[PDB]
Length: 246
Ligand SMILES: CCN(CC)CC(=O)Nc1ccc(C(F)(F)F)cc1NC(=O)c1ccc(C)c(-c2ccc3nc(NC)ncc3c2)c1
Image (tube, rainbow, N blue to C red; front, side, top):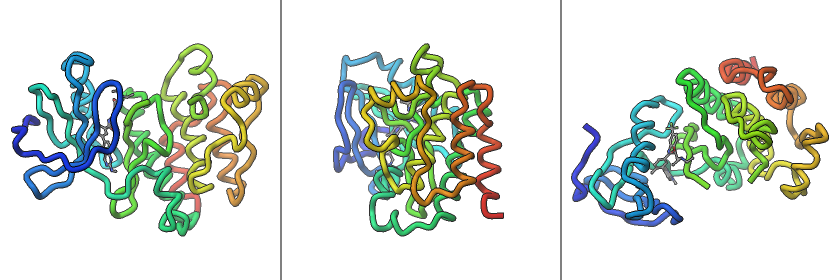
């Protein structure tokens, strides 16, 4: 029920390009704006490319970018809804994003946690949670997404032994929180990857960002407990963020 004739689409602007294909902004039947991921032929099997689509059919939730359609005849396409304000990391840097209050910022962080909770509920693992993979709707709501290919957001265990789990994602969420309260600042200000790698094996943790509440900073630290099983659940994180301001 997801297949649609290629004729229903018009690609307007290419958002990005890479090894396995391209991303375009377009329109479906001239009335709906959409983002389109097209596979560059003979770059990876149609099967492997469509696995992304099958995963999106599975994970439908208010806090996750939703799949709209698919075109299964080469050039193979994956069509989704389009978010006017783009990614969270970019938006926060605009005047519109800088003018946002700490209240609004925690509401957005709550929404992200809510979506991750969903992801947790479904035994899924994001592997790349960061503000760049967060889309901002036209109403400033937040949806979880993943565009593709950087150590700053990865938990130590994942970095060292490649152990990516939902706990690996919680840690990334902690990093993401720093992005949200500095309005787009890169984490570990001033440090190169090698430096963040070094500091970590020493138990170093990001210093509290300016204008970051003390309670919010401790929530981040919980997300950064060395032992993965010591990190909170996204459900607990959502709950705490929504009630942050009673
Ligand atoms: C590790 C990499 N893996 C493996 C391949 C990818 C993967 O598994 N992806 C992945 C994994 C999980 C989930 C979900 F959360 F739903 F469960 C979604 C996605 N994919 C996307 O987010 C996505 C797919 C197609 C398009 C067209 C866009 C997409 C690109 C760009 C956009 N810009 C704007 N506005 C500016 N608005 C909307 C979009 C949507 C985004």
